[PDB]
Length: 158
Ligand SMILES: CNC(=O)[C@H](Cc1ccccc1)NC(=O)[C@H](CC(C)C)[C@H](CSc1cccs1)C(=O)NO
Ligand SMILES: [Ca+2]
Ligand SMILES: [Ca+2]
Ligand SMILES: [Zn+2]
Ligand SMILES: [Zn+2]
Image 1 (cartoon, helix red, strand yellow):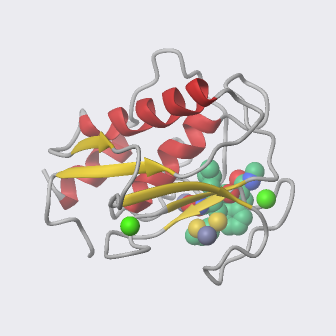
Image 2 (cartoon, rainbow, N blue to C red; image 1 turned 120 degrees about the vertical axis):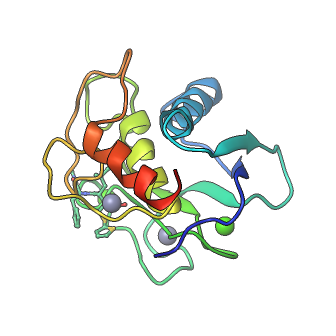
């Protein structure tokens, strides 16, 4: 079971998607990290440059990691378990339509799922859990972590 042995973790957004403003992309990402912080001892801090523990980027098809994206729909993004280098990093398929509405696909909810992986969680069979393998829209305005997900990070950290 891999976990971070440090509690303040830095993150960096390496590039952006044109469908959303830079401010909307930063808001989506920020809020997704907050979901996990309120249920664990982790604190996330944004750096504008340099080496972050968690790199976030929008890539297309082959992008250097041996797990190529597949164009519109299908796989939306992926993330690496806690660790050095690529460890903890999160990639989003630049070919998807990214939104901040109920329309396919809501960047905040997909980001919240990937960050679960960056922190060490695996998929859940509970269809109501954020860590479930298939994407499903749920209201986001005052969204909070499902109980199955809370049990999950609490079991790793505390
Ligand atoms: C509408 N499309 C989907 O719901 C696709 C379909 C899919 C799921 C699993 C396997 C193959 C295809 N799901 C995703 O894009 C997942 C992310 C969503 C929940 C935001 C994405 C799947 S890729 C991986 C498979 C196994 C380990 S990572 C993911 O878990 N990344 O962390
Ligand atoms: Ca990393
Ligand atoms: Ca895709
Ligand atoms: Zn990748
Ligand atoms: Zn996943």
